[PDB]
Length: 253
Length: 255
Image 1 (cartoon, each protein chain N blue to C red):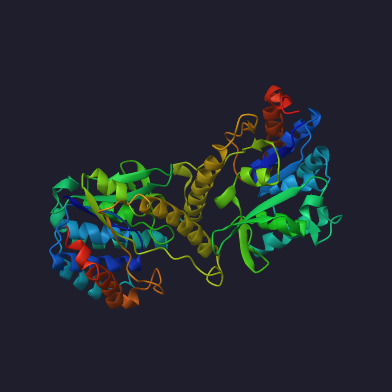
Image 2 (image 1 turned 90 degrees about the horizontal axis):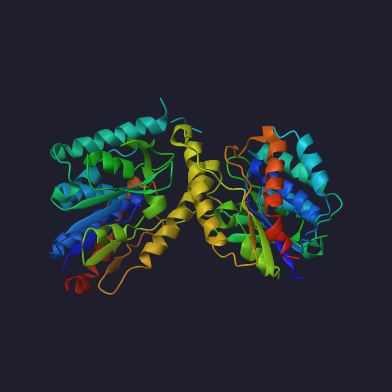
């Protein structure tokens, strides 16, 4: 049976995906397709390009997050540079099905609200577009479309993975926790909260489509902030432990 | 004769078109038995429910001083509060909104939970103010321990609320919520607002798809009308009036 891996969108919490990967390889579970949004697209796409979970863990641990003309523009440039540098070996690739593992990334066309699925082109640019959280990174233009992260239209792209032809999906949902009324002090917070609501709705809808055979992994991440990169060890381990406890069920694949 | 609910969709400047609708509705002798509204729909609808005539609403709108990738309003909230409080001095606080001249409901979003919050009692100016709390324009307001923004993102076209007021038929005014073009998205604020516009359109269409035969959708022709373009109040009001005049035959079938 063909196994697809769906990595949900997010920021810091998405580092938990590394853990999941580390556990999957440890259990000898072969992935035939990967679909991701934002940090799910980053981790999943780097993995799909040929990186090992150990390498991704190392990269995450040695990364200077705090460090990485409008601020969103600058940070967008930095994002692009880091991704391009990490994915230099895919320079001559154009077909995402021809990566080490077939890959899809998800963005939102900010002009129309349409879901945009990347299956071809330049992998670092697709990942960057999918990672382009509003108010953190400036929108990216690809093929005449202005694109932001896919979170607001398809944060958990189960059906994208299924469209890649797999029979079963392993779905990792890192969650998108709402803020308390004490953490909604500024306009930015209100806007971001609205986006969070949107994201949660489409995420719930996609999760409702899971069927017998599919495996849902929800790493224990209560208390972890969206921009909390000071706890990378715990983030990775949370994803790892949540997948390890399911080894009995995963083994049936 | 059936009980008629009026549903006034949310927005800002475009919401003034509601006045036109009202002007036509009264002119055709259509009795409204209940009103449910969001943001400007709640402002126009709420003022109307408190006894203001469409002519008076038009006069108010016409004489109002509305003037009060790049990176990105408590005072605005205070002034909105002031104008609403002034217009509604004939109603007290601690009042049942079903006891207004026309039963009224206003819709807001609990920004902490994302839950819909429907006002059916209390201080009318405060409820309308909450419903009008558009993020990035008006600071959120606190009511009964809840932090509230406008209801657009959860229930921009509150049809089921109107039905919950026990009406048989609804007249539903969708003044629309247009997306900005790619070329018009310049600030981060623009992007955020665009996303809000998207979720607003989603819930709006979900509610609109529930309209039954007998109900009547009125969709005013507001194609090129900016969401905060208060420089064309006459045109705005006329659009609502024209739209309701065109559907006169469908609406006549209500009474």
